[PDB]
Amino acid sequence: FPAREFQRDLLDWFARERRDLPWRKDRDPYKVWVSEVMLQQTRVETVIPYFEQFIDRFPTLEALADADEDEVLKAWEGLGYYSRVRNLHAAVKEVKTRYGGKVPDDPDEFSRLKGVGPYTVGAVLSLAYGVPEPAVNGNVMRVLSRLFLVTDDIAKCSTRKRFEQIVREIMAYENPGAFNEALIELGALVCTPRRPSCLLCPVQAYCQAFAEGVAEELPVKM
DNA sequence: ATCCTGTGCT
DNA sequence: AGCACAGGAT
Ligand code: SF4
Ligand SMILES: [Ca+2]
């Protein structure tokens, strides 16, 4: 696989098209983390004002850690999935109490926190700390399944481990955050669930699904 | 190594 | 009423 050329085309596209979303204002692991939790459950159009309101109320990890659960829930109200904010709240309290108030940059340690799974670990650590971990969410699974014609069920850990291995092989190690962000952004804007915009895709020349005319059949979910 | 869960959609 | 979605699940 011509990974360097792929990285060039993907990252050049990302340089031009990257959305100036609120959670991209800085690289605070706390803020990235909050935005990833919101985006896991809610459309970007709705997350935008909730994120700003949430971070206004709780600007830093310690601010959230120290807030009463009532205040946290009030800030979440309208987003639903309240157990997921309760878990975030417990996790940042644990960060304050056992991890010096700093999000661990060890994927293993960060993963032990309540609610924190492989994707959240990869997103937060690569975006905020530049740790070369894969950040494979639904968007990335769709992009990789198409590029590499992966027809395995994406609900399976074996399939996700394969996607993880692909990212580790093709990642731009000089900027893992940008690389991971770019794959997610491509999935959001171009390589969409239905009718992907293949004709204006920056990595079309690399894509096996486009070449075979089966992009809309991918990814495979049982 | 999942399959479960809250949610939205039709 | 039943299905799709989307990640973490121990
Ligand atoms: S060419 Fe189409 S299917 Fe392939 S990655 Fe680009 S948008 Fe996705
Ligand atoms: Ca975990």
Image (cartoon, coloured by chain):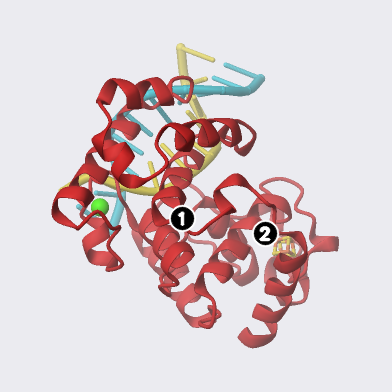
Chain colours: A red, B cyan, C yellow
Residue at 30 percent across and 50 percent down: it is A116
Find out if the beta carbon at label 2 lies less than 8 Å from the nearest ligand 1 atom.
yes
- Which quadrant of the structure image shows residue A34? top left
In the image, what residue occupies the spot 27% across and 68% down?
A106
Dot 2, how many residues are within 10 Å of its Cα: few (below 14), some (14-19), or many (20+)? many
Name the amino acid type tagged 1.
Asp
- Helix or strand or loop: what does disc 2 sit on? helix
Rendered position, A66 above or below A155: above
Q: Is residue A100 above or below residue A163?
A: above
Q: Quadrant of residue A3?
A: bottom right
Q: Position of residue A202 (x, y in %)?
A: 77, 69
Sooner in the amino-acid sequence: mark 1 or mark 2: 1
Q: Depth check: A2 or A131 in front?
A: A131
Q: Residues within 10 Å of mark 1 (few under 14, many from 20)?
A: some
Q: Is residue A172 left or right of residue A58?
A: right
Q: Which residue is mark 1?
A: A153
Write down the chain letter for disc 2.
A
Q: Residue at x 54, y 77 (%)?
A: A175
Tell me which amino acid carries mark 2.
Leu
| Residue C10 horizontal side relative to residue A22, left or right | left
> Is residue A2 among what the camera can see?
no
Q: Quadrant of residue A12?
A: bottom right
Mark 1 element type? loop
Identity of the residue drawn at 20% across and 55% down: A112
Q: Which residue was labeled with disc 2?
A: A186
A100 vs A103, nearest the viewer: A100
From the top left corner, tell me how far across and down residue A120 is, in percent: 39, 54
